[PDB]
Length: 51
Length: 103
Length: 103
Length: 43
Ligand SMILES: Nc1ncnc2c1ncn2[C@@H]1O[C@H](COP(=O)(O)OP(=O)(O)OP(=O)(O)O)[C@@H](O)[C@H]1O
Ligand SMILES: [Mg+2]
Image 1 (spheres, chains in turn purple, blue, yellow, green):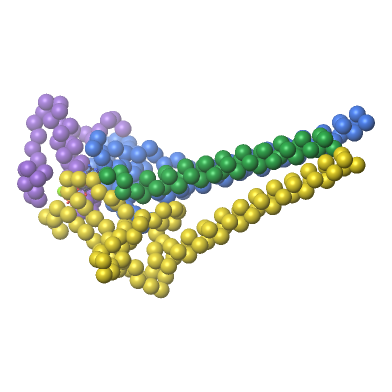
Image 2: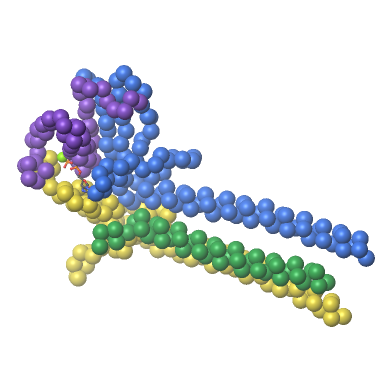
């Protein structure tokens, strides 16, 4: 309800390897960027080009 | 997790000799949300959730869903055949009745 | 595993009093891949995957797959026999009808 | 008797039509499962 999670909240994405947690995080970041807002994606697992 | 406002769990389960993807909101503070384990399927267009499962035995997913749909179609079709055969039977009885009346 | 780009899991399961081999790609970064637990069988020619399981109850593997195929063949054959017997029955009714007409 | 014969003819034709329809539906369901578990989605 409401169209999405409340702004400024902490959102956890849990799952086993290969579930799609990184895909969902990338979706969030891209959606935020498409609206003209800034976004940061701290990655401790992959390089920028590989991602 | 003790602090998180929202929780999204993504599952990749092995059932019926094949792997199916699903996701659900374990908790969403300060709002009401769906309580369904919505199966999704990632593709070039992005992440896309399949239409909600309708009918009894909603746990079925993947090939099992198509198999259940086919089984339902077959059974309901044969029930229709049952009713049609009974109607034809009454057809036959009425034909003899009024032909006898004609004689 | 936290870093691996691709993951291939090989299973050697004991089911139905016998061991069957299978393998599946747990994850393959940056591409779409099959989500089926493909049973394979190693031999002199090398590693060879069996044709995909078709039909309901795909979990069946090894001797169980052949048994299921045989059961399906038997049941569908007997359904054919059902339909043939009904056709022969209508055969008989029509024969009496037109023989009576001849008299 | 001729009325009986015509009824029987209708019954035979219903038998053929419905049986062929079952054939068609079985083929369609088999194809659907074949895609659902097929690798042709990629090549
Ligand atoms: N074009 C595509 N079509 C279908 N599935 C795809 C496609 N591209 C990627 N995938 C799926 O995405 C999966 C990887 O998703 P993702 O990287 O978001 O997972 P993850 O949970 O972050 O993984 P990890 O534990 O490795 O960090 C691949 O295993 C593949 O199954
Ligand atoms: Mg990742």
